[PDB]
Image 1 (spheres, rainbow, N blue to C red):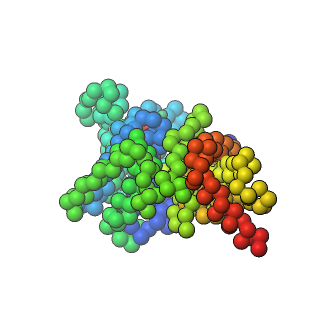
Image 2: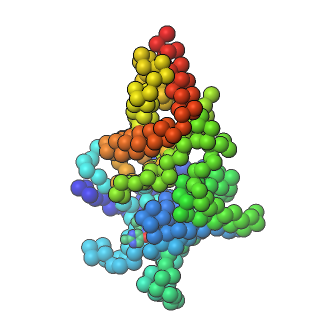
Image 3: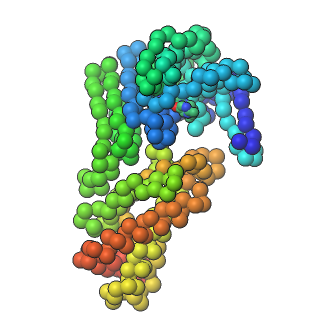
Length: 355
Ligand SMILES: CNc1cc(F)cc2c1[nH]c1nc(Oc3cnc(C)nc3)nc(N3C[C@H]4CCN[C@H]4C3)c12
């Protein structure tokens, strides 16, 4: 918030490849999903509905509070227009892109917002408003939501066809990580509907893709920070997420799982026996054969460099570590035969490193 930056859309139209992946419009669809996901994470949306039409438009709808429409004092336009028609960025010092990138790279965009008993409607073309915000209908006060339909512009894309298969993979991936979410998908070209809703979240996922029944951390929290995790050892899946988006280069949340596991194995070796007390085991050793998914839900996810691929928040590391240690120790201290096996294989990895 120290520096706030506001431009028009020309830099996006001039270098589309710096604001999206231009093979197809999927990344644009991702921008819209991400916003609707932020409304799920804030506790207000439970439903994300996606439609692919035969005219090659894409519609995404949620049942959240609805994108605000109040007039900005300084900019003299509604929230929906302000967010759609200008590039928003900023930070702490100089030297995610926003839905305006989708508006910019689209010949047409329509927004329907339900709030405060009103159905609002607005239309853009090539990133400029062309039909004013207007109340077109009325509705129950608790009938709320945001719905965006957009028409990707062929001049900015190698192909206007949506890659359906990757879109489906992505939606499933997200529904897995948020049990309070139900995602629906309708492809009117292929005549195909899907519904993803995972009541037990990640349960069973590792099994499908020691302990024999993998360990699950189920919605652990400290204030406005949430942790879901599943892991086991094996002879491979190693996925981590922040706010439902992959962190292919790990970070503080992973280091958190790593340290929390080490601490748990080290303490258990110390408090038991197993002829392993004299083996110099490392965090790396107890992590070596670990298969897991960890998914954290935090307030202001800070990342590495200028990209969003490695979580940096220096206090997530001990948020995860402490939780993993406590939960895993409890489990170790009620599963004797398997603890012993986990410990032994870990010692084996350590001895092979030392030799
Ligand atoms: C496909 N659906 C969809 C699509 C979409 F592009 C945006 C929203 C969207 N649904 C939304 N719901 C809310 O809800 C809010 C209401 N009030 C406040 C203060 N914040 C969020 N806000 C929304 N906003 C406001 C901004 C805050 C974070 N992201 C921006 C987009 C959306």
